[PDB]
Length: 154
Length: 151
RNA sequence: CGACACCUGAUUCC
DNA sequence: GGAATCAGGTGTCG
Ligand SMILES: [Ca+2]
Ligand SMILES: [Ca+2]
Ligand SMILES: [Ca+2]
Ligand SMILES: [Cl-]
Image (cartoon, rainbow over the protein chains, first blue to last red):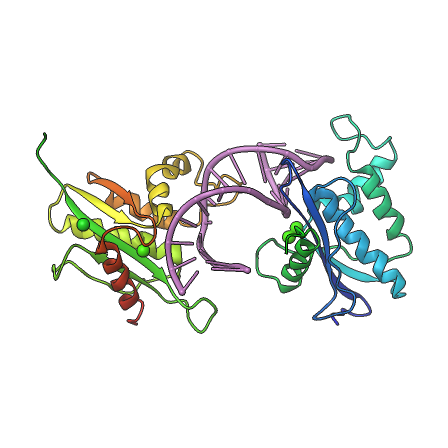
């Protein structure tokens, strides 16, 4: 199980097939290690978009971890939108009604709020991993996030 | 009706055993039975599918040059090379070669060199659906493999 | 404008 | 069931 000095490692990823198209199918994915018992591939409730799938993949992780009574983790992801939110954009947003830099409702509020609710007491070390750059951890989490939005066909 | 004016040529580029044990790509260009210019050498460089399939078009016309031929019909199954040369290049030339997604068009170095030889020359690209018609393809296609074997 | 993603479609190969 | 690669489009924020 990947660790990094008392910081248990974890990769997360979200996906949303047909994002911005008629019927969006979106799922969350979180990989803790090979054949690891915490590796989830859930489907994302409600709104179907990559952005929330992505930040919610991260929620699942934290949510999971707490249950495993782990307080500090190095959570990798390829979502800058999530990282930038959770560690910058949010703070501001709170002090001003969650209004975008163009003066309008911070769209993914509900999502970030949840996510921030969970950073509480946790010492997350948000790390970013490149796209299809070949990093296992991320590709296995990607793998998972799809099986989470599986078609149900077969 | 009308006369006749060009020469035909089939071209194929292949990339092997995906994994690591390998990734051998070969070029292969056919001009007809036993014809001298028929050749199927190995692809020099970053061994890949697309890339080979392109340079495999360079050699073609490049030899077309070494024959003072001014216009041919080039056959190929990859409409990446085709689309690339018949369209996406002018665009790439008017955008510092940026993928219609912000990043850099990887085979610029290739599509560049290719557009070079296209100079003065008049190529009429012909795409052929896999398992197309005309043995011509199965033949170039065959040298490719033979090429990929050389060191 | 920029940035990180999420896709849809194509063509070939095996 | 990918790897090659591209076009076109959304998700969202500075
Ligand atoms: Ca992602
Ligand atoms: Ca992904
Ligand atoms: Ca071929
Ligand atoms: Cl013929």
